[PDB]
Image 1 (spheres, rainbow over the protein chains, first blue to last red):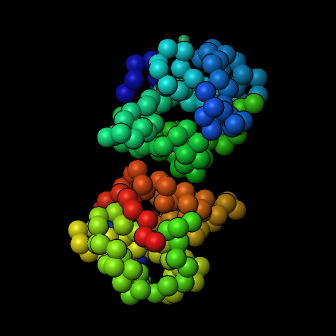
Image 2 (cartoon, each protein chain N blue to C red):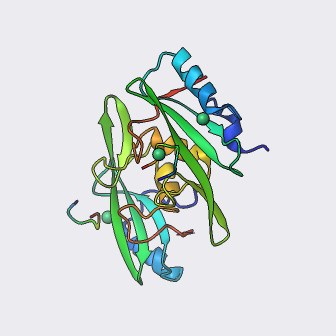
Amino acid sequence: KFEGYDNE
Amino acid sequence: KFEGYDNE
Amino acid sequence: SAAIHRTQLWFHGRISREESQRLIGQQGLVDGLFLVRESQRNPQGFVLSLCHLQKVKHYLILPSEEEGRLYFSMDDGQTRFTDLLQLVEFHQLNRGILPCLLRHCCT
Amino acid sequence: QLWFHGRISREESQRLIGQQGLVDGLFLVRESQRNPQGFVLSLCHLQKVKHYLILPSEEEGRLYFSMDDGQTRFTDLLQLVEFHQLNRGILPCLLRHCCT
Ligand SMILES: [Cl-]
Ligand SMILES: [Cl-]
Ligand SMILES: [Cl-]
């Protein structure tokens, strides 16, 4: 996870 | 899987 | 810089997130429409901007080093690529962590 | 390129890999003699040679190669090999050394 991005 | 091969 | 991804039609340089969203919106908002851009502040990092279900999502791509070899990843090293071209070519056929395939270069 | 050995047999692939050391990650790709439209990735792991079938497939008119019935798809054998030099996938180890 990366804050402000859609990675999951 | 495939008979005779090591794919798993 | 003269990295190979700079020869690719999906690479748009240092455009902003809002810019990428306008550019993708102007080209139809078609599913799988995508581009790759440089992060405005992450050293050597990139962002994959992708359209799916009329919504534009953004996936951070970060560099990392394993021993002395560099690789790029969107998932903290679960899936690793030597360069952005290998990452993009993989995700044209495999969804991976993405909600759909990369289908059309936004240009 | 240098990892592709054409239409050699399984026993020959094992002899070639043994002759070069039986090192983990040593591999070659050969045309399958028992599946003419397929290929075999022959790989050394833990001082043992294993063989993985690569089969072609079509979805929506798009051709691809896969070792796991389309869960992971590749446009060509080079892309499959390059992916597995960094990612294990279904393989027990990474592809590290090309077998001459
Ligand atoms: Cl968030
Ligand atoms: Cl923003
Ligand atoms: Cl065989």
